Each structure stands twice: as C-alpha cells, then as structure tokens.
Length: 246
Length: 246
Ligand SMILES: [K+]
Ligand SMILES: [K+]
Ligand code: NA
Ligand code: NA
Image (cartoon, rainbow over all chains, first blue to last red; front, side):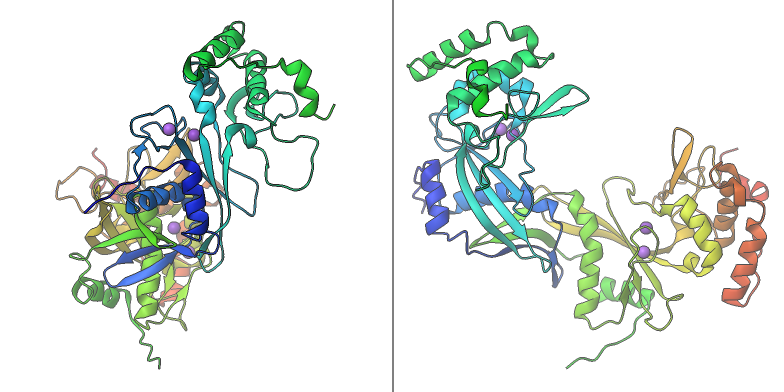
C-alpha cells in the first residue's frame, strides 16, 4: 500500500549520489501533444524545474515532507512534518558552465528572519550543477549539500557579498565555493563569521541601519532560546582580514 | 526509406483538424531525469513550444519545408523550398482564456518589409488557441488559418492597432477576430484596407514619417512586379469610418 520513511538531508544527498546515480544519469524536457513529441531546449526552464523534480523524486520514494508556501525565503522542503524548525531543505540549481546564478535571499528580509528564526541558518542547500548540450540532453555534472555560510563570502565595499544597484542593497549573492583556484576572497569558515558579516552589513546598509544597534544581542538571545546554547558572534572588524584582500 | 510530400498551409490546417484530431487531442510538458518524470506547469513556455512542435509534426510526416533564420519577421516556415516568396507559414499561440498576447511585427520593420517583399502580406497564420488546466494537461481549444489583415484592426488614435508607449510606436498588435460580439472596431475586410492603414500609420508615426511621401506609389509598383497585377490602395480617410467608432 504505502510505507512512508522519514529521511534527513544527508541521507537524501547520499541516496541521490549512490542509489539514483545522479552524476551519470541522463534527462530531458519533452512536450507531448497528439501523437508527436519533441525535445524542449529552453535553457532557463531547467533551473526552475529541478526543484519540482526533487519533489517528484521524494514523493515517488514515499519520503515524508511538507512544501514551503513562501518562495522568497528558505526552505523549500520541510523533511520533518512534526518539527518545522529542523531538517530544512533548500534546492538550488545553476548551469555549471557559468558561475552560480541563484540568489540566497533578500538581505532586509533575511537579516530580520534570522533573529526571529535562527534555525534558518542550519538549512541545508542541495545544489544541482546542471548542463544541457545542443541536442537537449540534461545532465547533473555536480551535486552539493552545503550550509548558507559555506556558499557565501565577503565582497569589495560590503561585509557580505550582495547585489547592490545604485547604492541600494537587494539580495545576498553566493560565491564560487567549488573552485580549486584560491582567491583572496574565500567562503566563510564557520556560521559565526557569516553571522558577523550579516551583523555589520545591517549597519552598512542605510535601509537596515535603524535596527543595527540591538542586532547582536537580539540574535544571541534568540540563538540561545532555540538551541539552548550560547553563541559568540565575533566583531566583523577583527575577522574581516580573513575574507577581504587588505 | 523516405517519401517526402509538398503541402500547402490549407492542407496542413485541414490535416491537423481532421487527421491529427487536434481539437480533441491531449498533451503535456514533461521533465525526465534518472528514473523520475514529472509534469511541468509553467504556462508561458507552452506558446513558445507549439511552434517547435509543429516543426516536429511536419518533420515526422516527411513534409517538405525550410525554417526562418529571423525571429523578428514573418514567416516561420517556408512550405515551398524552391519558391521562398510563396507558401509562407507563421505559427502563433495564445492562451485561449485571455485575449491574443502575440505580436504581428515591429511596425517600422514591417512597413519597410512589405515594400521590398509585398508577398509577405499573403503569409498564412496558423494560430493555436491553447489552454492548460491545474493538472498541467494542455489542449488546443481552437485552431485558425488566417491572413494578417484578418487578425488586425484599427485603434483609437492610430490607423492600425499598435503598441504605443509614451508616444513611441512599437509592434503591430492583433485584434480579437474570433469574438461573435460585434464591436465598433472590426477586423480589416480585405488586404487593400489593411495596407491603407499601414500607409497612413507610416505618416502618423513620427519615426517612419520620412518615407511616407512616396510610400503608396512605391508599394503599388512593388506589388505589380511580384504579382504581375496592379493593386489599388484606397485613401485611409475614405475607408476609416468602417473601422473606427466616429
Ligand atoms: K530563496
Ligand atoms: K513575428
Ligand atoms: Na520558502
Ligand atoms: Na521569421
């Protein structure tokens, strides 16, 4: 009939890698109508549909989950139906030939979110590095399971890597975590440093400066409630050198 | 092996209607990867892919054609490989629940094109009125084969229905030819009236006014060369009443 198992993000990662054999797998978008079917070669559609496909893959393996009603904020899937603060999964996809084109989240929303819901910082990002050839055959060249702090970095002029347009801050932007090329700007080494960057960015950004004063304390108390454990966020000025050039 | 037939636009229209049974047919976009396949419910992708599907349908029925290298101008298919001025096919698709969302062509380009290539006015438009339900099943609710003059009309403030933004003319826009509701603005009754609208629109539009003086003569001579037959384009002022309100 129906025997539904509960899985974690690491089990899903490992299952796709070993059991599905995702790295060697082949796939393609296809449109059927009447008695004719054709390949579909629209390249931008692949990234939006991998998330839907994992949905179908989970649902076909009887794996237990809920879906997120908010597209703007993480997560995409709740892997624990009874605990919606833990076992949280975000699916991301980008064309592997170029740098990662996905966004993490609007900075203003995310800086507020992680005070109210610090457990969002422990969301797992299942990232598909996909590729589509000229014939339309889609393949997953790379697959990753990473934390938000593992896929972001600092930038020039701001504490965290941002999308800034005409001096106005928008979305937190990912770095190139996978490159063996050792740049002057590496990814954040730990959660505390990422959060330290967020803290300072709150003050740097004129839009979010109004709630910069209390931010550190408010976050550390909120982390304590939800995790029953203190966390020490270093000052950005002390740790900035690890992530900048000079 | 391969027995390839030559068809005309009306034969293709009738074949789809009776032999394919397009009106009662069912279809859907679908993404395969590994061993999981899912429905794809992105609604904007359907319109772009019907054109590709007809390509596949022609190619699977051994039907002879060439494809157009220019997306901005008609046609999409050349149904006569030896005569690329005749048997020209444009495929259009719109969601049947709303009014037609497709464009005919940029007006500046099209006003110049029909002097150099008057045979473009005899292009056949195979128009798919499609629909996608909540489950993702695509159906062709209506199918039409029409001329450009049968799917356009006048508007308020210009001789032909246009997309105007801040007093700047862009694309020729289709009317609602299919509606049994008899509006004050009907579609053009014949080719000559459509062309009369184009002629006047050339002068009305400040961008194309520089070549408005000679336009009528230049067009009528060009029509004569290509068709070996004179054509009389009426003055727009005389016929405007048929297409306006007052
Ligand atoms: K997001
Ligand atoms: K066109
Ligand atoms: Na979400
Ligand atoms: Na074309």
